Amino acid sequence: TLSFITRWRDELPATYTTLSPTPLNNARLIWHNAELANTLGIPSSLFKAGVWGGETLLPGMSPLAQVYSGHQFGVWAGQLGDGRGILLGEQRLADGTTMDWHLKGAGLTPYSRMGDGRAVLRSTIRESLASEAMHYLGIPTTRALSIVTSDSPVYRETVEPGAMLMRVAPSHLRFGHFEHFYYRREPEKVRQLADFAIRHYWSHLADDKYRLWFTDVVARTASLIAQWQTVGFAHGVMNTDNMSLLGLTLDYGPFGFLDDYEPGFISNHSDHQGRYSFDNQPAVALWNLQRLAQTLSPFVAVDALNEALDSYQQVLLTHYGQRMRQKLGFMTEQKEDNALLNELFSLMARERSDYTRTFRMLSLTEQHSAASPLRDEFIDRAAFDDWFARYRGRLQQDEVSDSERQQLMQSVNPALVLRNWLAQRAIEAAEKGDMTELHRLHEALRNPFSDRDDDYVSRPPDW
Ligand SMILES: Nc1ncnc2c1ncn2[C@@H]1O[C@H](COP(=O)(O)OP(=O)(O)NP(=O)(O)O)[C@@H](O)[C@H]1O
Ligand SMILES: [Ca+2]
Ligand SMILES: [Mn+2]
Ligand SMILES: [Mn+2]
């Protein structure tokens, strides 16, 4: 009954290779996203490995692997592509929008570059948990519809079970798609991609279209990174092929949500220069946008490209600043705000304070009371009490009740984030065949702004 179309295949010829997934050995479905399946209109019967393991095609699907290129760790890498993933099809929804179904781990393709074409259970689980977590934090992201595991050995640092993730997203367009055809000296294919993107995702733009479009591409990336900074998400691999044109979080690998507040956090152990450290994300995404701008210069006026690039800073800082004010419960903008936040961040960094728990406990603040669960979390309690006294004194300038402010703060400061230790515990149980933890953790991550009475709100063990 579902409606699939071959929009990419037919409108962007010679940008992909058509092929089928390669099923794994004894593949089994271990989790699917019931809520997302409902919003997509997927009959519950389709989950009873089937399409989720690349073993069945639905009417209208026409699987293909896309080509693209990227700058990796700041240097041009040339062609990369869908080396282990396949766009099974584009699902048309009743409101006219369209959603990609991309099977990650689907098998060898022309872009596999001597790799095995496979994904592993631990990484499919992590990507499913982080992407769904990001969605319910309200941050744009690819979504996770299903995981299958299998009996197929896949060789990494150790042998792993081969697994597939069904990833859903409005598009998998990457900055690297544009770079691919620019460096392959195919400027009309770069322009075809741009016009495809505008037709399907910026359709309201009448035919100044490129200036307005690229200004909005910049805005959406600036907004994305501002959101990552506010929640403490470190991506770890901001290569240009992992930058979504639409401003979605894309390609969860060696990511991390902060536990202790560490501005220079390096989540990716292969990032030996810290290029993708947490505090570098805003500079890196501007550099990525600058590389994307270069590809558009054959048909977008340079003044327009630079007007868009110039706006990145203010879009990012306005989003970040307004969001941090919400997190602090600053219900009017005041001059001392920036200094109070710098003081708090300095306190947290020097105390190695937990990021999420600090803001969640701060949401319990009673402006006329010096008591707080935060006091016990600081070794230097006097320094904390001093900041907290000045913070509450400033809160009083808003003239807002504790009830109203706590409601706001609890609506924007999550009680829980997808910490590495939580994902790892889910992985260990799934690997032994027990999916209860994976399901329970997914359920909790759908409700990040509610308090909990279990250990999903707990810091990782010190040892
Ligand atoms: N095991 C693998 N076999 C084949 N190609 C791979 C494999 N792992 C990574 N690649 C390719 O190497 C390039 C860089 O990897 P990466 O940025 O980690 O993408 P990815 O996780 O495979 N997929 P995506 O989430 O779609 O970006 C991309 O072209 C990948 O498709
Ligand atoms: Ca610590
Ligand atoms: Mn990638
Ligand atoms: Mn990856």
Image (cartoon, rainbow, N blue to C red):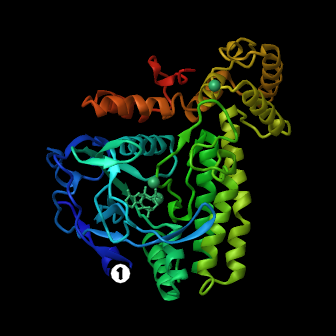
Judge by depth and name the residue closer to the eye, 38 or 287: 287
Judge by depth and name the residue closer to the eye, 232 or 308: 232
Judge by depth and name the residue closer to the eye, 133 or 93: 133
Looking at the image, residue 455 lies above or below residue 126: above
Residue at 47 percent of width and 49 percent of height: 252
Image quarter of residue 385: top right
In this rendering, position of residue 179 left or right of residue 42 = right
Across and down, in percent, residue 60 comes to 20, 69
Looking at the image, residue 110 lies above or below residue 249: below
Across and down, in percent, residue 17 comes to 31, 75
Picture quarter with the C terminus: top right
- Estimate how packed mark 1 is, as few (under 14), some (14 to 19) or many (20 or more) residues with alpha carbons within 10 Å: few
What residue is disc 1 on?
11
| Residue 347 visible, this orientation | yes
Image quarter of residue 330: top right
SS of the residue under disc 1? helix
